[PDB]
Structures are given as C-alpha cells and as structure tokens.
Length: 83
Length: 99
DNA sequence: GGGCGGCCGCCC
DNA sequence: GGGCGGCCGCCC
Image (cartoon, rainbow over all chains, first blue to last red; front, side, top):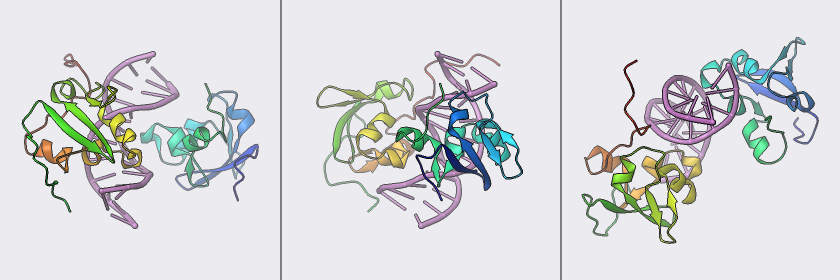
C-alpha cells in the first residue's frame, strides 16, 4: 500500500523492494535514503544498479513508487527533487 | 489507415506544412538539418518548436516519437525520411573530432 | 560524474 | 496509432 504523502515510500526497482526516506533524499543524492528488507542502505543510483538498471543511468525513471517513476512523483509535488 | 490524407502537398519544398494532434505548423527543412535541438517548426502565432517540443505541443508527449506523431500530408515524418523527402536531423550541430 | 534529452524496439 | 521502457551520449 502506497501513501504518496507519507514520509516513507515503498519503492521498487527491477523487482527489488525498498523503503525510501524522503528526509534523507532531501539531503542530496550522496545520502543513502533507500533501505531494503535485509536492512541495507542505498543511494538512489546504487538502488538503480541493485535493481539491474545500471545501463539506464536515470534513477528518477528507474526507481518506481506504486508503479510511478519518481519523476512523476516530483512533477506532482509528492517527492522533493534533490538539487 | 496508414496512408496520408487527401490534400495536395509538395514533399520536396523547403517549407512543409506539418501537423501533430490538432496543431498546425511549418517545418523548415534547412533548420531541421542543423540538429535535433534546433527550433525548426513555426506555428501560426510565430512561436518556434523543436520536433520533440512540437510533439508535446500537439498533445502527443506520451508517444515519445516525433517521427511518428508529427505528420505531413497525413504521412508520419518517418515515411518522409524513408522516401528521401526529409533529412534525418543530426544529434549535434558540429562534426565530431577524431577520437 | 550526474542530469536528462533523443532514439526506437517491443507491447497493447 | 498510442504508449513507454532500455539504453546511451551530450554537456553543464
């Protein structure tokens, strides 16, 4: 279940599940903000690689929330776009 | 279905009437040849668009392929290219140096 | 290095 | 014909 407004977002990338912490993402892409079910932590690009999508080189499209690319979440005000 | 419309259009002219959705514009072949990021399509209000900008203006952003969503005489621009009526624009506006 | 636009094959 | 995901290279 997905609440777009929640501080924690369930995300997927190539079938790998994670939990994204918006507060950590807001600190910039060098901060690990996505935690997988074994407790490990990933930056957005690291999670893109983890999900098999290294070649796409765009975590904003490769990482999904409820099936939506994170880019769509940013476009609709649900997720900060890190500067 | 896949064919063009019934209007007469000269496919060899330097300026082509193009359409995307309901939106009409004029494509300047000489500008398209310069590179894909060059504004080459002028709408009637005078505003200018690149091919992908024109696709978005025409309501076809989701298509992500101006070669099929932009038309001339009903024909997709891909058909115009396949038959030598339209150049395929370069990605960049200069010749790459030996690498 | 990273953002992001362009290409186009594959699906529906 | 609408749709969109995988891939990659241009450039800030």
